[PDB]
Image (cartoon, coloured by chain):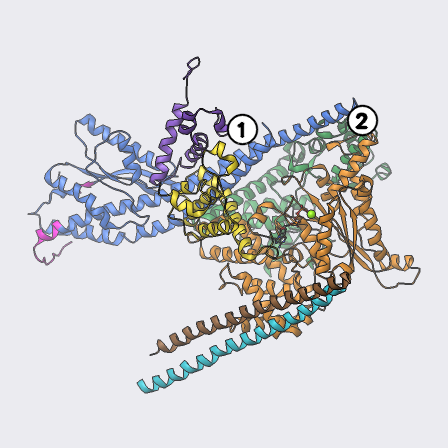
Chain colours: A purple, B orange, C yellow, D green, E cyan, F brown, G blue
Amino acid sequence: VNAGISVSRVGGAAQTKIIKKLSGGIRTALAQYRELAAFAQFASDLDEATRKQLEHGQRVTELMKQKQYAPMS
Amino acid sequence: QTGYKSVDAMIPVGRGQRELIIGDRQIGKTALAVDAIINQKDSGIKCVYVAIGQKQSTIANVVRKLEENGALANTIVVAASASESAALQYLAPYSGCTMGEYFRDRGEDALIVYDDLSKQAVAYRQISLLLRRPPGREAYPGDVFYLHSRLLERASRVSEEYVEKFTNGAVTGKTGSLTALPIIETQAGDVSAFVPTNVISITDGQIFLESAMFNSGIRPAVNAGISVSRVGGAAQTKIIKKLSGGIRTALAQYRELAAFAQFASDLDEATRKQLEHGQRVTELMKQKQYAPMSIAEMSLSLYAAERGFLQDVEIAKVGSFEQALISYFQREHAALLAKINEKGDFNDEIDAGIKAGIEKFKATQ
Amino acid sequence: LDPLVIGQDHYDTARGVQYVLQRYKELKDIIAILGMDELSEADKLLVARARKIQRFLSQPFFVAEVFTGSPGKYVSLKDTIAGFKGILNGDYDHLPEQAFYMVGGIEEAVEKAKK
Amino acid sequence: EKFRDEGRDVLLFIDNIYRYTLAGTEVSALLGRMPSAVGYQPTLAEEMGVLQERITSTKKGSITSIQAVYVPADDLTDPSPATTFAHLDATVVLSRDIASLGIYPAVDPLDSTSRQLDPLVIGQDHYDTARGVQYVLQRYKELKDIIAILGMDELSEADKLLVARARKIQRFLSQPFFVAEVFTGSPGKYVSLKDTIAGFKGILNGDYDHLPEQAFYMVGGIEEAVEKAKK
Amino acid sequence: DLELAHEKAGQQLREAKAQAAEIVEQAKKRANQIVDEARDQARTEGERLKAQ
Amino acid sequence: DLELAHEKAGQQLREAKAQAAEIVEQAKKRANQIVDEARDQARTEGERLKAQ
Amino acid sequence: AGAKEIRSKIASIKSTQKITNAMEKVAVSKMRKAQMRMAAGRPYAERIRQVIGHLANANPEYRHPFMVEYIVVSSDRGLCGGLNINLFKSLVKDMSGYREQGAEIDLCVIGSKGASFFRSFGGNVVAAISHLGEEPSINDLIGSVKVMLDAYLEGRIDRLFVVSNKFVNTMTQKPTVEQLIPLHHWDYLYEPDAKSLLDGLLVRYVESQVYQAVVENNACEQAARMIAMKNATDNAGELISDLQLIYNKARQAAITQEISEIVGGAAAV
Ligand SMILES: Nc1ncnc2c1ncn2[C@@H]1O[C@H](COP(=O)(O)OP(=O)(O)OP(=O)(O)O)[C@@H](O)[C@H]1O
Ligand SMILES: [Mg+2]
């Protein structure tokens, strides 16, 4: 699923209270992480803010991966 | 004269020439042609503006601007707005041309602007496909080249013998003319489209406006590297023909050595000298809308750059330097500006006179 | 958008923002091949302001709260001019790039940098 | 065709061969014919062949043609350029850069070509002389970028000697025309093929290495360079 | 030489004040020119506008 | 003292140049008011003539 | 997918080509600066060789260890034409001969790429410095050199060699290794003692040959970069030329399709 190009025109109204609060701006944050990675590929050491965002982005990307026929409650 | 330093110095337009204004949407095509009409209020050239497929409120803002600048009394405005019949939009350029041909055939000079020949082509395509005429490339009829060619070959300069034959002897010794400034819109810089290709091949020259230059603050947006006038120096007064030669060399050198701007320290001195000259001449070409310049006022700016008077001016102060220099000469050298404005003549006394004024300007202003 | 219709201060701010973003559209590819280090200091300094201005253009809207999750914001043209002028002057060059994303007025950006 | 039948060799100048192709496209659309690739007329190759096949060397006379060529969108694979190039025996390219140097003929010796530049047609002597000039002019264009980026001292003795012959060759390619006396301020010259081959053959071999390059500018035959030199 | 230098300096010091004040004199003539041509421009816009 | 003799010329010249620039800006400010005040007076009479 | 995407790619490659063109000329200028800094150190080296020579000969009773029976130089920036690899390929070849002969090897790393080559293979080191300006100063090398001279004095090292590229020419950068340690009629007056002076001169001579080596490798770095940026500019043109052919095919194909659709609809209506 390409999170930058994909979108829901119902948004947070189609989510339960728990998932709605926990998943706040994750798609727009993933859309920005995909952009930050390409820019910082050949640059010198950047600030803590940049290194922290780049590290946090590689983890939600690995989490969104799932096997076929294995749904989650 | 169009009143623009970039056009009048490098892409000169002569009486009876056909110069195309070509470029994308919203980059100054209309502004350049309207300012060329405004500059004729004192010249002797009658002007015609033809609006094809425009909205009625846009045509009214141009007329309000022709009236605010005193150019309306010298202009005929022909309108065929977007809600009007495709036949009227197809015929409007020929009606305006016919009104412009009156002055040419009687020994006088006229200027005509066709604000969108691409909208005339679109109106002629509508009529043709509805008459069921066989279609060609981009669905245009087989005679779309003949449509624009039949119109644009009327813009011409006629000899004294044609004017004496037409006037039956009444007017003698005078050659009449009709100069055309057709405008065409390109889609995303594609000059290879069918209608643009036809008109580029019919005209005597082209002024190309670019979106990248317009967004980089270069307001007139004229790409001088590809724009050309086949008439050239024959359409220039003696003073501007002498000072435009070096301006061409400096901009050409700037187009070649412009990446080194970020490595200018490491550049060789000769090249570093050329690089700043190129950047100062490039900043001189920037001008404002509704501010046409006269032959004398353009000559001060071109002379100052071409004779090296900007080497101690920060590239960011070149404009205030130009504006202040013209204001100084308008007060202390009014007689010299009036002398240059007679015919744009040049000699050793005018050259020495301008030099003395610029040296005195630097010493006190 | 004409100094004779609005004013020179507004017009200069708008053309200033456009100039910075137009120049950055060409350095973007330069940074992809090679690296950031190979740029000149003026280009390195410009790239930072361009990325911030791009982010400062983002404003959370009340009608989009269902999608954004955050509260909507309303910015007066005065704040719009003030903030962009300051960023172009380089006053907020001390703030991380992430602080201008969806922060209404520049003031908020100064507060988001602390979180 | 009439003059050729008289017993003459004739020149046919066509102002633009692309406009002949476009006029055929326009007429084909007016007659309602189904358009071909890139929107050209279905008869594109036949209309070009009907015109170009009359221009030939017969047993009475010969019509030779000089045709100006336009390339749409700078694409040499477009049907119009493609079809025209199939009937061309030579390509003369005029260069804006060469003109700035001051060589008024302005023909580019590296980009311009001919199908007659074959030893089985013009003989080994004409061919070797022409290929020698092109070889020297190519090396000089590479060396000029070296001289510019790194400097003139970085070159070998053989390379600096080649640069001196290349500059002499480049200026000897200039010539005063009878119609250009108003611009050049000097009388026109008609050099023969024999004088042309002999002049360039000597400069490549080094027979004129002592003369200044300017002596080889706007002179006509090689003996005139030798005389412009004594002065 | 100390007194002679004090005199040389005393002359150059004061002459520069008079010369610098003349820049302000050119500025006052320029200010008058801006205002006089503005009055003529305003008169021109007034007679141009009322004609419509 | 030879330093002070050019420093008090250089400083007073920058002050005089600032005064010259101030004189010019005051005239530019005076100029736009002279033009737009005449426009409102002319427009008012044009509308009065139309209404009457 | 279409003609739209190819125009963006041709513009992308054309922008990168113009800067790599300038970087070749910037590199040539910097190469000429590093070549004059190479020549401003020869007098101090040729004269000290004469003094160290004659002073030993007139004082045979003293035979300094340096006169009887690796320092590696690398760049701080990229864009080199495999200049670091070619030397690192000669460092590995010589180290092999000693590992075969049975000897151990201690190393001194100058520059960033040297450290990268050792962190990437878990290599040992006894001294290291990087971030030296394109204009280096002998004072920075003193610390790194001292860790190596003492070794040879303490027997911790039996032989010392400097590994650097040599500026053979504008087109040639020869990787080489040379031994730093071990190395008329009338006679000199010695103050305070000859032995006191020989100890001082030998350290000045080794620290001098090391500085000569660093500066020459910087000139090699600039030349190598010039050729790499020329190669990159040429390669970009080849990509632009290939993409332009694909763009012309896409342009011609789009026109034929539209005409078929126009003709097809007109043949129905
Ligand atoms: N010196 C200038 N020259 C030209 N345009 C300028 C200049 N300075 C500012 N501009 C602005 O650029 C814009 C150009 O609009 P214009 O109508 O002339 O463009 P256009 O290409 O003709 O647009 P369109 O294609 O819709 O007709 C206007 O907002 C104009 O005020
Ligand atoms: Mg318009």
Find residue F52 and report its horizontal and vertical position in percent: 78, 63
Compared with G133, E41 (above or below) is: below
Q: Which mark is residue A9?
A: 1
Residue type, label 1: Arg
Residue at 44% x, 79% y is E16
SS for callout 2: loop
Q: CA distance from mark 2 to mark 1?
A: 50 Å
Residue at 30% x, 32% y is G89
Q: Which residues are magenta?
A: G180-199
Please, what is the dominant secondary structure of the magenta stretch? Answer: loop
Q: Is residue D51 visible?
A: no
Q: Residue furthest front?
A: F52
SS for callout 1: loop
Find residue A38 and report its horizontal and vertical position in percent: 43, 34
The residue to which callout 2 is attached is D33
Q: Is residue G184 magenta?
A: yes
Q: Residue furthest right?
A: B168
**Number of numbered discs on residues:** 2
Compared with B130, B284 (above or below) is: below
Mark 1 Cα shell of 10 Å, populated few (<14), some (14-19), many (≥20): few
* In front of the other: F31 or B233: F31
* In front of the other: D4 or B288: B288
Residue at 61% x, 52% y is D100
Horizontal arrangement in the rendering, residue G54 relative to residue B282 (left or right) = left
Check the picture and name the quadrant holding the N terminus of chain B. Answer: bottom right
Find residue B33 and report its horizontal and vertical position in percent: 70, 53
